[PDB]
Image (tube, rainbow, N blue to C red; front, side, top):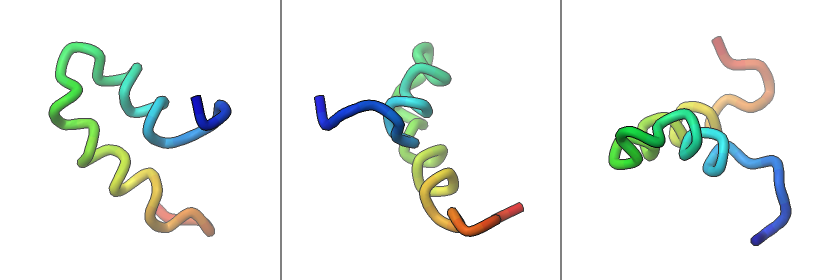
Length: 37
């Protein structure tokens, strides 16, 4: 489980139709956590 609240699970559910692109979402969502654009 690794607990809840993560860019992974978030990007996974958002891309349920195409989980193969989740990486692109996680990479951006994760990076620049201090206050990215």
